[PDB]
Length: 127
Ligand SMILES: CCOc1cc(N2CCC(O)CC2)ccc1Nc1ncc2c(n1)N(C)c1ccccc1C(=O)N2C
Picture 1 (cartoon, rainbow, N blue to C red):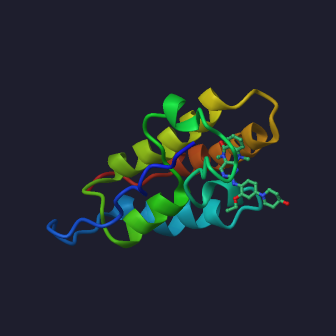
Picture 2: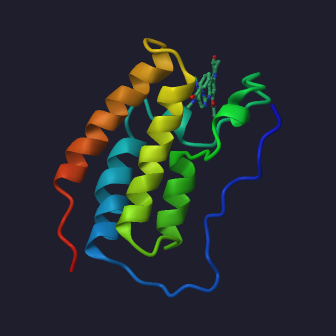
Picture 3: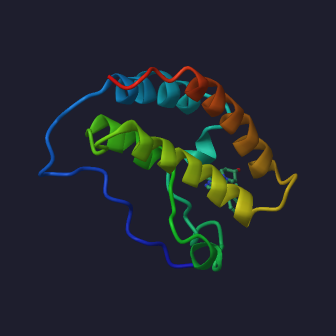
């Protein structure tokens, strides 16, 4: 159940550069998901020690959570919006491939993913 080090959230040697899409991902997508009543399991990395999940990080090879994504967006870690979208997708995929369907945590992920996909439908165009 040992936990990996937390993912990196800052890149000390990349330029500070926004795009309209990255602004949208932070100020619309992340903001909306973060305040949802079902966000709390996803606001920090899975703690396999405290949740007693010895197999979690043997099955989940790319851990991801919204706290990491939030910090990455705030620190301008991503070079483009697609890297951020992939992190969201990884977070949901991890939940769905580890947990049993109908588990409460899967229902929570499904509700958050619906909101995520609706907001991504309105992602502004590259510019
Ligand atoms: C920072 C606080 O974190 C928690 C507190 C409590 N508590 C608070 C108080 C109550 O009275 C007692 C339970 C329960 C869970 C979490 N966290 C948490 N993080 C990640 C996961 C998750 N739960 N669930 C539920 C999972 C369960 C099994 C296998 C995988 C997962 C999973 O995929 N995710 C995303």
